Image 1 (spheres, helix red, strand yellow):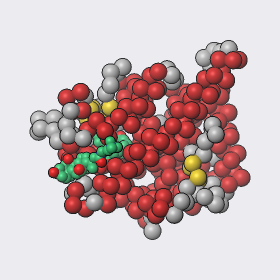
Image 2 (cartoon, protein in one colour):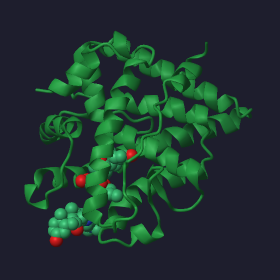
Image 3 (cartoon, rainbow over the protein chains, first blue to last red):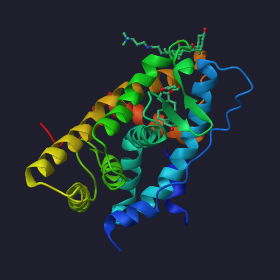
Length: 13
Length: 247
Ligand SMILES: CCC[C@@H]1O[C@@H]2C[C@H]3[C@@H]4CCC5=CC(=O)C=C[C@]5(C)[C@H]4[C@@H](O)C[C@]3(C)[C@]2(C(=O)CO)O1
């Protein structure tokens, strides 16, 4: 899993 | 607004390493500090990529794929630029508070790691690369590798990549410029782009070794540890297609 990268791409900003 | 002006406005602010110059240097201390700096630069690189026109139109899996493949290329190229702009000397300017000088270069095993990165800055200096050429070249490095079996949005990717190639062409033409000298310059800059795969291969060898050998006690922050963990199996399964301008 690539939890942090996916979060940074999906979050607003 | 022009495409290159949009690439310019999203340029990340320079980050500080938070390196205490009153404490003596060591190779381990510098490598450890740089991994933490790298993690923060990579978080800023995600925000940067998201604002690149076209990038967000690719499938989310492709966005993740491209950032994971290109991370070291992006870091070394931006470092090459900061080093080239700071001085004409053989210095690596990782951060304004963490510059690898000639005294720092003499630390055990500093030079063998630094030589590949010094090659990037020396080449930008030798070719007298402009800010507009640099901006186009850095976006092209994000688009320099794809999976063996390609992307989910392959067609759209090829269109976006061609657009930034034409954008690099437009930057070259601004200087000011002779038709023959333009093709010569295009050839040179794309040759430097191609050579980034070789620079990165050398940097990842050290990166992967220091990440995997836990007895070295070299820490990587979560952002870098996650990328490295994802990338190591992709290299071992041959799951990488390094795009080249010259065959
Ligand atoms: C002077 C020690 C260099 C030796 O060479 C390896 C490649 C390094 C990255 C190069 C690109 C970069 C540019 C930056 O501005 C901030 C951080 C990074 C991203 C660098 C760091 O992470 C450490 C690095 C991963 C490396 C290592 O293996 C340590 O374990 O250090």
